[PDB]
Amino acid sequence: FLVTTLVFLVIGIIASLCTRICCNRGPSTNLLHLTLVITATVSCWMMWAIVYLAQMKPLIVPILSE
Amino acid sequence: PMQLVQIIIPIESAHLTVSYLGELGLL
Amino acid sequence: ETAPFFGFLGAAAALVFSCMGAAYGTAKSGVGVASMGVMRPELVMKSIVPVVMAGVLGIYGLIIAVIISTGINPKAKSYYLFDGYAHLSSGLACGLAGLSAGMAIGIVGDAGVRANAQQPKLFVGMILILIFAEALALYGLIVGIILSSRAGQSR
Amino acid sequence: ETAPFFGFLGAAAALVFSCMGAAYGTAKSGVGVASMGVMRPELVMKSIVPVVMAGVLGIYGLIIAVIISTGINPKAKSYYLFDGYAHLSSGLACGLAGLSAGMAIGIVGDAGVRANAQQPKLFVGMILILIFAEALALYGLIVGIILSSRAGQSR
Amino acid sequence: ETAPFFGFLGAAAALVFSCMGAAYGTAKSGVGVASMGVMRPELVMKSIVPVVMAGVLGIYGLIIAVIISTGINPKAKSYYLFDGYAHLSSGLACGLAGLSAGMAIGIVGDAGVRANAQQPKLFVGMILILIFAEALALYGLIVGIILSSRAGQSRA
Amino acid sequence: ETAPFFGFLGAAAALVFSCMGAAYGTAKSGVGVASMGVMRPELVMKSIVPVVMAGVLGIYGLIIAVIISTGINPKAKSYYLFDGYAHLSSGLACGLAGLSAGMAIGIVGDAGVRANAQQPKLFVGMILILIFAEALALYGLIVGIILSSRAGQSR
Amino acid sequence: ETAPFFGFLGAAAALVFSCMGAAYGTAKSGVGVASMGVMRPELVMKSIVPVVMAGVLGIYGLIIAVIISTGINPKAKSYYLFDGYAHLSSGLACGLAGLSAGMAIGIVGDAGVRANAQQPKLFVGMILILIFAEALALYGLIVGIILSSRAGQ
Amino acid sequence: VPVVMAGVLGIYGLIIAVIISTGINPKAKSYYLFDGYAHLSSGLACGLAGLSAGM
Amino acid sequence: ITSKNLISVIFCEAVAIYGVIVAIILQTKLESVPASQIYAPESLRAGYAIFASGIIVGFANLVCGLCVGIIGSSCALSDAQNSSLFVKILVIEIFGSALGLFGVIVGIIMSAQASWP
Amino acid sequence: TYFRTNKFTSAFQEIVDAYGVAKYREANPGVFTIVTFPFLFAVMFGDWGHGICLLLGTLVLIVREKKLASQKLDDITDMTFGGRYVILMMALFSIYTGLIYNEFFSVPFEIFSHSAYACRDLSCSEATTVGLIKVRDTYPFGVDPVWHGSRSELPFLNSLKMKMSILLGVAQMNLGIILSYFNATFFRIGVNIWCQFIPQIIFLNSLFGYLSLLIILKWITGSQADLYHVMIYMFLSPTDELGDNQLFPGQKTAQLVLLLLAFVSVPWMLLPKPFILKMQHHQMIHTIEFVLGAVSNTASYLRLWALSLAHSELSSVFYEKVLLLAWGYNNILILIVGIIVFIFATVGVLLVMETLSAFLHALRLHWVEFQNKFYEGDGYKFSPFSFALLD
């Protein structure tokens, strides 16, 4: 879902803006917060990408006989 | 980002500096 | 057919092995607890945990055996080798896990009995190791549940 | 056919294993009781409790074996290997559980008798330990009952 | 048609042997830690590591058992004769690897707990030894997975 | 019919034996390394090599097992007896050789760890001895691989 | 028929037995050498005869196994249960003889290491003893080679 | 000297085995189950007695 | 004592040579035994005779070798103890070698056993 | 020396100290690990219900830390006081992890629709049919419950989880290589960095990346019968030729070329640096270290997959016990007793046992990854003349 990727990118941009507003004073602190935000975005996007790759095409469906 | 430091301080004054730097200190 | 010979044997073996292992572990733990109580009553009160672990292992083995026995429905299920084989596998797994857990629990109980006299913090820490061993036994029992559920294919 | 062979074999094995375990437990308890009496004849009176518990467990195993054996009536039901297999499994499980419980309870009782000779609260500790050990015999009896029911479930 | 009995037996045996090896290793490590106790109370973090390794080995065994159980589906692709024996082989390999790893881990953990009381600078070396030991269990799990992979092809 | 099943069983037993030998060697090396680290932390770092050698032997056994697994191919040939026989023989030989070499290397490393702490000079010769021990297992693995390559038994 | 299975089993048993015997002898000799080297590291460097004998035993076992494997040519000979049974037994006997020789040589070298540590005369004496043991192992290897040659007929 | 005598005893046993090999031809006499069992049992008893005497 | 042990090793090498000769003979002593005709009762009798010969040869050779080894060990110890006592040790070594030679002669006699077609 | 540590940074600093030390110029990935270890642990396992409850308890502890400062903690409580921030971050990550897993309160829950995933068509056909189930609508926030949490969907879901864990391990190795390159740039070696880190890095990275790209290509093509074992089938032949299943038209020759390149790079990982050192005038440890590290990364991925499977199995067991208690209790008392017992057992299993096991495994994987990456121990802590009682 390209829409999901765009939403994740927008969330990352919002987080970057929040971190900048919070700690623009400490340039090293700001860089640390930016690195943390980047890592969180990478992790979330990778998880969603794996989930969608599962949904790309199902090998087989489930059986739940009583 | 630290480095070594060397100094000569009179003992009487060194007592006050040591007392001040006791809680946290640098070196 | 030959299902009763397999299923009954597995059901008996699970309980037998689990009881033997739990008994050995409880005996070791009781010897250690007696030593600790001779040392100090507080250590005797503390040393109850290995007995709890042994009882938990025995209860898990009994539960697995009960589930296996309840699986035996010859009137509803036609006599298949697979149906008895699943029960036999579940019983063997449960019994082996119970025996191993009992031996490990006895060793850990002796160690913790020594530790309680040595230091209360040591006993508190060894509680974590005992819990980990109990968790391994529970994992074996859970695999036994999947083994029992495998019998569903046969009818 | 050959089902009575298996059923009678299981009935005999139950009693044999229960007797062996009771013998081991009684020997250990007697050694502990002799040690306590040598140390203190007065305290020896309370020391008989683990021996009584071991004897009770042995009798319970024997009673369960007798009950299982009495169920086998060839005139009552036609030749079916399921009933014999179930009876044999019940006997084997009950006997093995009783033997393991007896041996462990005897060892724990000897240790607890020594500890009680040392300290008084150790007597209560050993009583709790033996109560914990009785869980093996309880599980064996439950498994025997389940197998006896499965024997009637044969069709 | 009688293969599923062998398959179920192998599936149970894998878990049984893995649990036995893990229990032995855990008991050895716990005895060693309790011996190391009192003298080095701060070494609780170090003593935790062998229990973690034993738990990892047990989890690997359970995973192998679950995979083997999933492999046994008689409804489609009738087990024929190769399926049960393949499952038995995979289960035996997994169980033996687990038992060997458990024994080695228990011995090494006892040695490390003994070394914990004096000169704790070797904690890194002890952790390295534990990881090298668990590598054997990882290789065994990989081998079991590879064996389970070939199961489907034999159906034809 | 079921002969390649026996071959696959032997292939699995190969990895099992290799893992057992590697684990024994690693345990001995770990005991020696613990002793050396107790002696001096510096000797501990140089003493890691035998553990790596045992792990490499185990990895070689795993690779041989994977190759054997790749050897089994239903589309290659129909049910044939020789496919199972050759594979089982190769696996058994490789596993036995690996286990024996691992035990020998473990004993050698256990001696060498203690030896190196007293004198660092002998560590050079100990390294050569361990290298020869590992090379024996490597030759055994090559011999086993030769048998696996010997696949075209029929036509 | 089942002859290739018997021959493969025999060759595998030969290789396994030879490897186990070589491993046991090498372990004993290496333990002895490590113990002896503690006193004088200079003498330890000379103590390479254990490595030499271990390598010789391993090479002999590998060569025997390779020769046995080469004998298995189904295209060349359809073979017979008699021929396969003979080849398997011959190979297994060769491997067992090699294993016994290697174990004995390693046992001797275990004490020979300490003897060499004592004096160089004991060192050369143990060298001669190990040479005799290696000669026995080579005789066993030659017997196995002759047996493999007989399998061709 | 007693060691030499004991070795001579083994040499005599070897000579007896050589005589047995000379008589080993089976065409002359057919041995049934009873004959083979009798021979094997008697030989085993003699061997046990010989080993005990050697000890 | 090393020379005495060398004499013992020479006896062991003689035993090995006897074994090699036995193997060569068994290679020669093998009957016709056709691949097709490997089921006759006469072939079974020949196989039983050959197996008996091998069992009588190898077991006796191993027993003689072990006896020679123990005797040589004791003899080397005694020679280390007393310098004069060497011929007595050589006597025991010769006795062990004679036992090995007797086993070899037994194998040589048993060589002519096969009766397979 | 030690980098300044805030309240949140203290736990990462303690972890880095556990992983030995590093030089002042040496790169310290402790700050990165302060998120990576929560990132891996969330990938490793997580229960939405108790995990949220555990996070709430940790937050309450952080709020009451003022009293906890006065009230001295005991044993593991003392460590928890220091690691509150790290635990909270890990639980926050595990929240999204459970959201992906969809096992809210250790149980699947419908998202957005009445049923997140359903069976299109096959109204009369059983779930065990040729048509079986069609997921016309797929859960957009998490894995489709029909395709993951259902009875027979377990094997394919587990295989997919393992495949994804392999890619995650590859990414972790790539991050370690990147950190090594960055630290080498900080080390400021004129050519030694290119001679040593570049060959040691990149080689095994591309080796695992071939498999990762094969997994991605399989996800694109969607082969069914091989499940996640198509990669195993492809890699089963290291020799040339064949390669029918290759999704990329030239994947066979390209794979052979890549194998040759890796074989050539293998000495390049070990040879150039000692040669440069000799020209100016360890590698033996570096020998086989690449293969061992790749095996370790695969082991970490498999451990994560196994931990996830075990967590799913435990959640299923707890749900089964709860369902059995509820269904077979017409009276309120029996249901209440069963629910309480199941809740206590599930809490003990998950919040304590499973949580500790997952934390330990994730920590060990983190130590392996960091040791592979950089900083090689070799240091000590900052030494001021601070009053221990006062500070």
Image (tube, coloured by chain):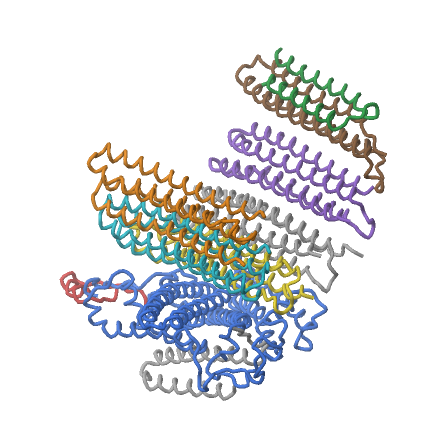
Chain colours: B red, C cyan, D orange, E yellow, G purple, H green, I brown, J blue
Q: Is residue D74 above or below residue H46?
A: below
Q: Is residue B6 left or right of residue I49?
A: left
Name the foreground residue: E14 vs H4: E14
Q: Quadrant of the C terminus of chain D?
A: bottom right
Q: Is residue J207 above or below residue I95?
A: below
Q: Is residue G19 left or right of residue G75?
A: left
Can residue E111 be seen by looking at this rendering?
A: no
Q: Percent from the top left, x then y, of residue D29? A: 31, 38
Q: Residue at x 48, y 86 (%)?
A: A4
Residue positioned most to the top: H1
Name the foreground residue: G148 vs C63: C63
Which quadrant would residue A58 be assigned to in this image?
bottom right
Q: Percent from the top left, x then y, of residue J1? A: 33, 65
Q: Residue at x 22, y 68 (%)?
A: J68
Q: Percent from the top left, x then y, of residue E71? A: 58, 65
Name the foreground residue: J261 vs I113: I113
Q: Is residue C84 left or right of residue E153?
A: left
Q: Percent from the top left, x then y, of residue J287? A: 55, 58
Q: Is residue J205 left or right of residue J115?
A: right
Across the whole image, how many numbered discs are drawn on residues?
0
Which quadrant would residue J234 be assigned to in this image?
bottom right
Q: Residue at x 40, y 77 (%)?
A: J104
Residue positioned most to the left: B12
Q: Is residue J198 above or below residue C138?
A: below
Which quadrant would residue B7 be assigned to in this image?
bottom left
Can residue J206 be seen by looking at this rendering?
A: yes
